[PDB]
Amino acid sequence: KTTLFCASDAKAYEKEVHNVWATHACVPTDPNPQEMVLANVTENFNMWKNDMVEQMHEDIISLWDESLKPCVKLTGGSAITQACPKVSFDPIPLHYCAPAGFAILKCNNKTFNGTGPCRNVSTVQCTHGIKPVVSTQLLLNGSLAEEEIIIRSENLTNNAKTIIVHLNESVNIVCTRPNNIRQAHCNINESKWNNTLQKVGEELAKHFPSKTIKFEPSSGGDLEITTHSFNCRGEFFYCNTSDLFNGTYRNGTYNHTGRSSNGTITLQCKIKQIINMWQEVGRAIYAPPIEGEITCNSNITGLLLLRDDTETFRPGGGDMRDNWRSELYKYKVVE
Ligand SMILES: CNCc1ccc2c(c1)N(C(=O)OC)[C@H](CNC(=N)N)[C@H]2NC(=O)C(=O)Nc1ccc(Cl)c(F)c1
Ligand SMILES: *[C@@H]1O[C@H](CO)[C@@H](O)[C@H](O)[C@H]1NC(C)=O
Ligand SMILES: *[C@@H]1O[C@H](CO)[C@@H](O)[C@H](O)[C@H]1NC(C)=O
Ligand SMILES: *[C@@H]1O[C@H](CO)[C@@H](O)[C@H](O)[C@H]1NC(C)=O
Ligand SMILES: *[C@@H]1O[C@H](CO)[C@@H](O)[C@H](O)[C@H]1NC(C)=O
Ligand SMILES: *[C@@H]1O[C@H](CO)[C@@H](O)[C@H](O)[C@H]1NC(C)=O
Ligand SMILES: *[C@@H]1O[C@H](CO)[C@@H](O)[C@H](O)[C@H]1NC(C)=O
């Protein structure tokens, strides 16, 4: 309803670019945060219509402008060139705070789906620390649901609406370009992936009860959304997930159709230079990869899915606002 401000442990000393941006965009985190439980009250929320999401989106666009400058930016006919140094890039958590006269209501219901009424409600000055992690298909390094896997959607019957799966247990994904210089790969332990998809299939089954639940790779589109794309220490990884979203959940049981090897699914990745931008319609060109071993060890904490008897789910993404919603879903600004 108003304009928020951000708070962070960004440090002076870092040249890591999230730290720099936060040092002159945010105020320091309050060591002593106040929170007010009101477990009787009940109010409504709508994670799909939440202007904290737009405010954070604009912040992260600004952060990426200042921090990950492309050598060339193409928007339509016009090309902007500027220096594109390699930088140290590691997202840090950001808190969104309501200014004087306003508060932030947090919904305390462990299983709240992001929509409708919520009984146990607190009031706080700032959100928890949210790392602004840009990615598609898999949500990385978020915070897990406390109880059961949660299915979030603006409208589950409308198959054009992105589904956000909030995981209650993280799944490790290690992606590495080892010492082709654009060849990389990610390793996921097939045991845990098997489990979490068994559980996601269970919850989806509750919402589509007659049907068989199939997971399948992304149909089509730009590489950014048909692969699991993300930024790892400045470099843009594009990781094939057809061995990942590839399985059937039938009779209360999940069976993985994807191919593994000695207990691990391995995704084949490329580090790319020409990027379809998430900030706006346009292209960005960056310099070739830094040297040595580029490795990110991340937690998968959620999924972005799109629904096509049988119901069929494929990985989605492309609108980074859904990434922010997945963390902001339980907050509302008031007063
Ligand atoms: C939600 N389904 C609709 C949909 C599908 C696809 C997209 C949108 C929307 N976009 C949108 O809403 O912009 C507000 C985008 C429009 N930009 C464009 N065409 N150049 C596009 N997304 C990306 O291009 C994208 O994510 N690139 C990407 C780059 C670097 C990394 Cl590390 C990364 F992880 C991802
Ligand atoms: C979320 O809960 C509301 C009721 O609180 C319900 O109307 C809506 O259909 C639910 N959505 C999902 C995706 O479960
Ligand atoms: C996570 O959610 C699933 C189903 O939503 C449930 O079976 C499981 O017990 C939950 N908690 C875990 C695995 O810790
Ligand atoms: C979502 O589903 C359809 C759109 O396909 C329509 O009835 C309406 O927009 C929504 N329905 C409900 C029950 O929310
Ligand atoms: C992923 O790999 C499979 C098999 O290697 C291939 O058929 C598919 O086209 C790839 N997807 C993308 C988006 O490159
Ligand atoms: C699942 O993986 C197998 C083996 O990698 C592949 O042949 C198949 O095409 C994948 N499934 C789908 C629906 O693409
Ligand atoms: C996720 O967090 C870990 C630990 O901070 C970090 O090493 C990793 O690179 C992060 N992943 C991404 C994609 O930022």
Image (cartoon, rainbow, N blue to C red):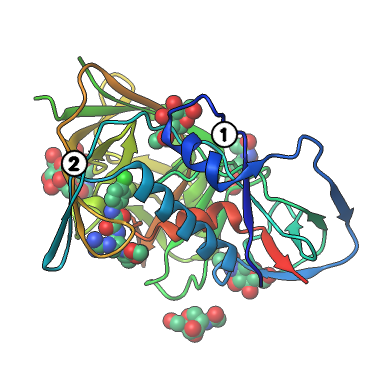
43 relative to 172, above or below: below
Image x and y of residue 271, in percent: 19, 35
Q: Is residue 109 left or right of residue 38?
A: left
> Contact, CB < 8 Å: mark 2 with mark 1?
no
Image x and y of residue 255, in percent: 37, 41
Q: Quadrant of residue 218?
A: bottom left
Q: Earlier in the sequence, mark 2 or mark 1?
A: 1
Q: Determine the quadrant in which ligand 2 lies.
A: bottom right
Q: CA distance from mark 2 to mark 1?
A: 26 Å
Residue 273 visible (yes or no): yes
Residue 192 visible (yes or no): no
Disc 2 residue type (three-letter) = Tyr
Disc 1 residue type (three-letter) = Ala
Secondary structure of the residue carrying tag 1 is loop
Point 57% across, 68% down: residue: 51
Q: Is residue 246 left or right of residue 168?
A: left
* Residue where numbered disc 2 is placed: 286
Q: Is mark 2 within 8 Å of ligand 1?
A: no
From the viewer's side, name the closer residue of 184 and 129.
129
* Residue where numbered disc 1 is placed: 10
Point 20% across, 19% down: residue: 291
Numbered mark located on residue 110 in the image: none
Point 14% across, 30% down: residue: 182
Q: Is residue 112 left or right of residue 239?
A: right
Image quadrant holding the N terminus, namely: bottom right
